[PDB]
Length: 185
Length: 179
Ligand SMILES: [Fe+2]
Ligand SMILES: [Fe+2]
Image (cartoon, rainbow over all chains, first blue to last red; front, side):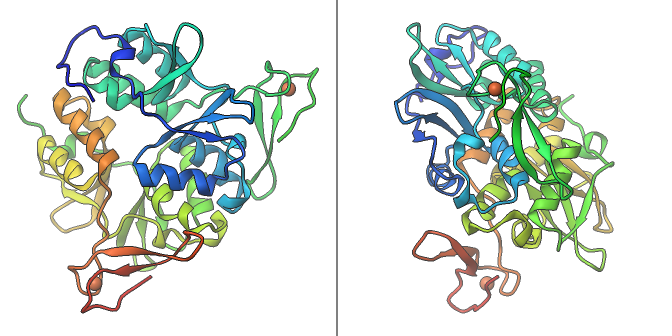
């Protein structure tokens, strides 16, 4: 953490966490959370088996998408829980622009990618709190409580994955909203 | 102003759940209400704890059990994190940061929980530095679950070969409490 002092403007790249951790998408919720608890890191980058960055696992994603399934954490691969596609902003974004992105999506952290598209870090509300106005911080906090990230289907990439519940309120599957797509997970 | 008592900004319209409610049912309540902090009461009306997202990630997931098989009494922050209603927001901030919390209960003189106060509530009256402090402490520190029997030891996780929490045991050698 490079000390920089408060400034109205600030390039995300300069304040993001370059020492982020990446986990495989088949990692269980149990094993992923062990990593979070151990490192006191509540945001992990998720890659598929070919090295593609496919999502981001956060605390809220676990509370919103894992718990409702009502299964043991060692029985659910994080691919079914992570925010996907991976939430992200460009490394040259000002903190203000990053704030707007997080708020628009109800997030409190996202990945940062460089021009060629590589994930170079993770930026959180904590990171941003040193530069954002108090009003901007409250906005992100309120948006995170009230809004949920829109997860897109990995099969057609266009449809929105919506939850399908049963009589117990359990999430049986998340189903692609795309009429032309028949995907469920 | 340089002053503002928490009672004025707290949320007096909060949700309370029984301590035998499963993590599954408690989370469904939180998800449906978009309120990620519940006050927990026992079967005798006593406020015994506060269930937060972090308490679930730290004290539920590691047990590797279905959400409907674990009662929140074993997950919630306990003893209940709290501040008096006459506390200045700066004092509430110090309390949260000292405890690695982002929210806590507010009690009146008699001692009953009258509301819940969150970082979002405080964000409108705290300095930028204090807000950052609370965020840093919530990430770096975790609430200390003081032992209810000896009152001085702290309940520590006891793991099996898989790294699963079997029980939380008091750190006090002179004490034999565990849950
Ligand atoms: Fe689809
Ligand atoms: Fe003890």
